[PDB]
Amino acid sequence: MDIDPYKEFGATVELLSFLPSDFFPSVRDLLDTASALYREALESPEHCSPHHTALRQAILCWGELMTLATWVGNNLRDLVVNYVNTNMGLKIRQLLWFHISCLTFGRETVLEYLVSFGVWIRTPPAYRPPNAPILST
Amino acid sequence: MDIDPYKEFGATVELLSFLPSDFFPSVRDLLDTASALYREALESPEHCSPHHTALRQAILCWGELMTLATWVGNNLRDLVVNYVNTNMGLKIRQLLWFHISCLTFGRETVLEYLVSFGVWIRTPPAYRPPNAPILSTL
Amino acid sequence: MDIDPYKEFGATVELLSFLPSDFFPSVRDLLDTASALYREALESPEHCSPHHTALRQAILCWGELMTLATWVGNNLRDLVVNYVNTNMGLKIRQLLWFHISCLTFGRETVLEYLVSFGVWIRTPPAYRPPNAPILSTL
Amino acid sequence: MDIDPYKEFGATVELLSFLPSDFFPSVRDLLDTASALYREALESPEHCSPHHTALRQAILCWGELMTLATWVGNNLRDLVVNYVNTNMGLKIRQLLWFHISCLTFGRETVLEYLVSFGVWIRTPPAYRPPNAPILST
Amino acid sequence: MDIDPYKEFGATVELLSFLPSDFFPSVRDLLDTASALYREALESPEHCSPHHTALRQAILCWGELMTLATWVGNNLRDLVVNYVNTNMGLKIRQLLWFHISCLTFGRETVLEYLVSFGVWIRTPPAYRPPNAPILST
Amino acid sequence: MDIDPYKEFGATVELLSFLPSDFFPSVRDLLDTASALYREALESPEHCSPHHTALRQAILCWGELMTLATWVGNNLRDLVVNYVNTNMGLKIRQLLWFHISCLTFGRETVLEYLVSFGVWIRTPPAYRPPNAPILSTL
């Protein structure tokens, strides 16, 4: 079956395909952003939103992938570090970026950001404004 | 930080720890159970439960884990598959079994069951009833 | 003076002497069980029960012995640990079995269980029914 | 699992470390004091307080600590006797002093005294009441 | 004990860890900004906000640190000037920047600025807009 | 500019000047007094007083000052410690004592006390009562 990670949140994997690969900050930057803002909330047992629930799972799913990559790098191997942190870690960098942005800025603002980034990224460089659109408030 | 994936649901990882390894069916058998009788719920964009939101992530995580075992397979190598499906896949099977059971039976059926299994399995086998507590709809 | 710790709970150490000594599961199995579903209430300052109040003191007493048991194994040696975790810890496992089950299953039900299990033990084994009485929530 | 045994009684382990350590009368004196005038209440099958329940564990814990320290002194062996009266003794000696005082004077009288006494010894002697405060009924 | 300087003001030391070290203007720039805007208010004995109270203390705490660094540089030593004005003075540059910003722009705007800066600072440089977000009104 | 840290509180630095050096306990003894019986207030994010806001800054300032004395210690050197804890630490001890006293006793108890100590200590010892005015709850 084809479980769309985003479809319940009003987005889709085609919609985050507007964002480039090297747009997402690294996993360490996301987790610090999650820890500085929602450390009491993610470890809270209260349901405030399903954004928290998809964030708790994705943090632990990254905790598995570093553990397996540690297991490979100690038993089998430097290419594996290059593979996981780039080609597999991008999908974690999508899910971490999405729910941290939705909890901070609202679901509605994020979905309008993906369209507004889409205009920017489709625009030819000669007519593209110099700064990328960035989320705030 | 330390995040308990069950703490939302009135359960803890210690409560799920008393279940043995073989209590869980194989990882394919959970996903087939998910895909057969919750597929119209999972692929729907409706938040029908916090379980459904939580459950979708587990498929996507396991499909991510099997991507690497496939990758390490034809790049380097089969001992890795013995490590994932056995040692690390149990955490997926805990995760998959728990939501599917809470979706099929309710939380209250499962959360009473994990206690009643806990008092069962902690008892030594000389004093233990020979039949394990099964999970029923009551 | 000799204080019976179970006396104020409708029990006595006679009634817990019905149980065989190996029936009580290991200390880690009890401590994880109180950490499973009572970790909130134990660290809570709310007087919820005397069973809480007793159980807080029993954990801290248990952690105090292991602090001294590792001290002798650091400064004098594991026969000491073999002495504690068999003989003095057996009295500790009696409390941790007691108050956990009285909170989880009701104090009245536990007191009936001690009587009902004693019937099962004092029955000669050839006429003993194969299932043991065990606590659950049916 | 971090349990502060005084937290339900409106104190902390820190607030009882706030007193000087030699302030606390000896463990033998505390065991005789509860046996003097609470012995019928401790042997009673009816708690009149959670203090009674908490205090009954404290003898039975200290029965275990003296048993083990005896057992080491039977077969090995006197470092342990001084050690258990250095760290393990003081924890019980705070604990036995607290509930015996709470059953005698009430909680609020004790808890105000703990604040009052530790300020008194942490006051320079020329600018304080001359004699130490002591508990009043 | 771990006294968080910011926790009562809705922020935390993890939240100002989003801001870089060389983002904060020097102590002389903050004190002139405090003197040009709040000289009558800081020396006023009226409580308008606890932001004033934490600002009066932090100004005097900097007045101590320059006095001690003057004392070292005249009695013991050029490395000390490099140490205090960088590694110790940063924490004063945090507290001075925070309360001057909160008194001028509102507490709510400052806390939304730290999140909005966090997006900017986590963003990869190729997709980062050229100007940093800056407070106004 | 010149900022009086006490002017908010109905006191001045001149009013706190009449207190001698030895009237204040040692700096550890103030912080231990703060940490023992106001720790749940200070570490809470609630503005319960302007004193609590003011008091938190003093710990953080003293921890900043002791960072340097530790730094000058293992870099260069012990005469500096004699300068901080004695000459400059008194300004911390004035600051720490004042809020802790105003929290424990009220402002009005302290502000009457600093006057009654002022008329006491300004009087020469031949005419002075031999007992210092102590600070009491009245």
Image (cartoon, coloured by chain):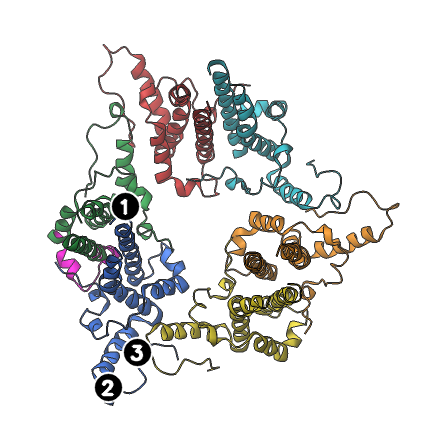
Chain colours: A orange, B yellow, C blue, D green, E cyan, F red
Amino acid type, residue under disc 3 in the picture: Tyr
Circle 1 or circle 2, nearest the eye: 2
| Chain for disc number 3 | B
| Chain for disc number 2 | C
Which quarter of the image is occupied by the N terminus of chain A? bottom right
The residue that appears at 49% across and 72% down in the rendered structure is B107
- Badge 1 crowding class, 10 Å Cα cut-off, few under 14, some 14 to 19, many 20 or more, is few
Q: Is the residue at mark 1 from the same chain as the one at mark 2?
A: no
Circle 1 or circle 3, nearest the eye: 3
| Res E72 seen here | yes
Q: Which residue is mark 2?
A: C125
- Residue A104: image x %, image y %? 63, 51
- Badge 2 crowding class, 10 Å Cα cut-off, few under 14, some 14 to 19, many 20 or more, is few
A39 in the magenta segment = no
Q: Place residue D62 in its image quadrant.
A: bottom left
Secondary structure state at the residue bearing disc 3: loop
| Closest to the observer, A53 or E57 | A53
Relative side of E18 to D71, left or right: right
- Badge 3 crowding class, 10 Å Cα cut-off, few under 14, some 14 to 19, many 20 or more, is many
Secondary structure state at the residue bearing disc 2: helix
Relative side of C131 to F10, left or right: left
- Residue D40: image x %, image y %? 13, 58
Callout 1–callout 2 Cβ contact below 8 Å = no
Amino acid type, residue under disc 1 in the picture: Glu
| Chain for disc number 1 | D
- The magenta stretch is D37-56
Relative side of D133 to E9, left or right: left
Q: Place residue B20 in its image quadrant.
A: bottom left
| Closest to the observer, F7 or C75 | C75
Q: Which residue is mark 3?
A: B127
Q: Which residue is mark 1?
A: D108
